[PDB]
Amino acid sequence: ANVRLQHHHHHHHLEADVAFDESFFSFGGHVGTSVEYEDKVTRGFNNTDKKEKTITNEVFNFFYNNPQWNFMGFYSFKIENREQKEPGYYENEDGIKQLFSLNKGHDLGNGWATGLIYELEYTRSKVYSPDVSGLRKNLAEHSIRPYLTYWNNDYNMGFYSNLEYLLSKEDRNAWGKRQEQGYSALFKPYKRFGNWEVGVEFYYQIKTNDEKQPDGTINEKSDFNERYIEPIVQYSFDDAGTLYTRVRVGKNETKNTDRSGGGNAGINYFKDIRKATVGYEQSIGESWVAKAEYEYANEVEKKSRLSGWEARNKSELTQHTFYAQALYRF
Image (cartoon, rainbow, N blue to C red; front, side, top):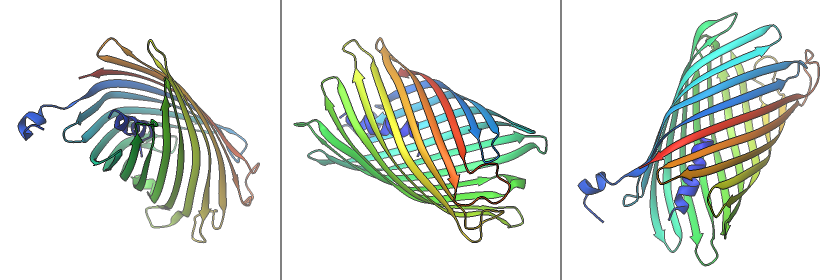
């Protein structure tokens, strides 16, 4: 699932007959632009620093929805540039990323609703390194999410919930193929009181990883699971903006099979995750919505057994993300 979009799906629901022809011209929504800067330092098992910098230019993001139809959609176009530096290596990656999302809802009455989300992200990119010049990578990520919601007006509480089937298939030409397949479940109880909103996201995911070289040699065959809990608090100022924060605490595990490629056969990876986001959103006059967001992320990984080459059983990622967004409503 696309994280930024998923929060739109959640909170648009909270925003809550003519003939087809008139209805066809009754979509509202927005058109907008964003920029995201991501500063990544990973101190891996080699005890050295892998530094990564990514700028994402969203030239167009399109939200459209039709209340009578109980139907929303989303399209996105992004240009992506990544530079990676580490001792004795570098890697530059340029890409175009498209996102398609469809949401069909259904009102079940008395607070209940249900629906289907289908979401598609295609990414194509070229990589430049000392060893490679213009290696093509094609990523297709499919996300199908049936959901179920409830809201109660007397108590101004409810929840969001969904399952997800997730499929990602990346082709990296000379570097082989990687397919990830899996399921997840999300439960998100939520409550509003005065200018406050509060919720907690509960999440679980189980996934399968398969990565082969072109000649069919197995790089990785592994099982993965993740869980996290993420409280969210939010406060709207009477005049007028909205400040919000998310804190995530999570764990995941990657357990390699006997068949896993050099040299991870039967090796387990354990990762502790901690994330913090602060954001502020404000409408400007009647049409424009502006948004800025900062996220800190820290992830620490250890493996079940050292193979022999590692300088330390510890791999730590520190990540800063900055995001700005301007949206024009219609």
